[PDB]
Length: 404
Ligand SMILES: OC[C@H]1O[C@@](CO)(O[C@H]2O[C@H](CO)[C@@H](O)[C@H](O)[C@H]2O)[C@@H](O)[C@@H]1O
Image 1: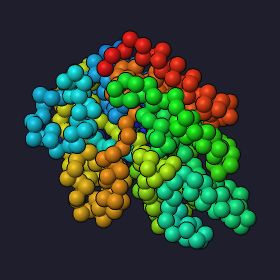
Image 2 (image 1 turned 180 degrees about the vertical axis):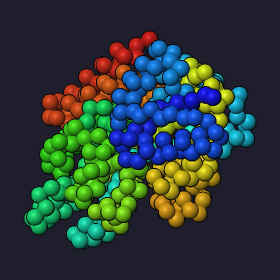
Image 3 (image 1 turned 90 degrees about the vertical axis):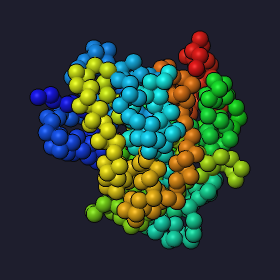
C-alpha cells in the first residue's frame, strides 16, 4: 500500500528530528501505513532551498512537509488547501493568529504544529553567586551583569566562560535575533505590516551598534558564526551566564547529565528602556500536505495526527516546545513540567513577527538582506548607521513593485 514520506525538522537540532520521525512511525503503526522520514539540514533557510527543489520538480517523493511560520506566502502553490478537511470547530482549537498566518488568499496552507518565541535563558546559580536577585530587564543591565560575572568566573579559572551567547551567523536566525534587538530599542519592525520600510532610524542603528559591542567582549568572537546549537552548546556546558534562544533548549538543558540541570530560568528578553516594547520574535512550524502528493487523504490524516492534542502535548512535555492549541497551556502535565509556559504566555502572545506577511513570496530575499547587513555590523565592517541605510536601500529594491 502507499508509503507516506515526510520531511520536517532536523536531526542536527536538539531532539526535533528524532522525535518527529518517532511520531511519524507511531502514526504508521497505529493506522497500518508504511512511512519514511527524510532528514533536513539544521538551518531553516537551508531547508527552504532543499524543499524548493522537490517543489520545482513537482516531486511526489515527499507527501508532508514541516514548514516555517515565515513560509506560507512562499510555499502556497506547493500546498494542498486543507480548509475542506477540517470543520470550523476543529480549526478553532488552534490560535487564530497562526491559522490566519497560514492562510494565504483564502487557502489554508498548513495546520499549526508548534509556535515559538525568542527568550532569555539565565544562570540562576551564577546570578545569586554575584549578588543579583533578578534577571536583567534592560540591555545595559545584561551587559553589566555579564561583565561582572565573566570577570569573576574567568578569575576563578574558567577560561571557556562568556557572558552572553546568541545567534550571530549569517542566516535566518540572525534575522530573528536582530528583529528583537531593533524592536526592543523602539526601532520598529524593519518592514512594517503596512509596507513601510522603517529600519533607517537612529534606534535601529543603536540596536545594531549595541550588538556589535558584545562581540569578542561579553560574547565570543565566534558568535558571528553561531546558529541555535552553537549557542546552546556553550550555554549547556555551563559556559554562558545568558543565552538568547528558543523554547526547545529548556528541556535539553534539564535532561539528566546536562551540566546545567536545575541551574537556570527563562524570562523575556531585555529592552533598551522601560517604555520600549518587549521583543520576542515569533517562530514556529506548520504541517503542509504537498500539492504533489499522490496520497492526499492519507497525508491529511497524518497531518491531523501530528497536530493533535496528544502529539502536541508530547512535544510540550518532552521537548519543551510551545503548543499551537490554547487548551494545552492549561494542561496540568504541560504546566508542571514547564511552569514558564504560563509565566511567559503573554510574551508568546505578543511575539513580534518578521515581515513575512508583507514581503510574501519575496520574504527570503528580504531576510537575506537583513541578515547580511546586520552581520556586517556584528563583524565591525559597518556601523549601524550605515548598515540601516544600506538595508533600507536593499529592501526598497527587493520590494519595489511587490504589493500585499
Ligand atoms: O526545526 C525546528 C526548530 O528550529 C528552530 C531553530 O532551531 O526554529 C526557530 O528558529 C528559526 C530561525 O533559526 C525560525 O525561523 C523559526 O521560526 C523558529 O521556530 C527551533 O526553535 C525549532 O524547535
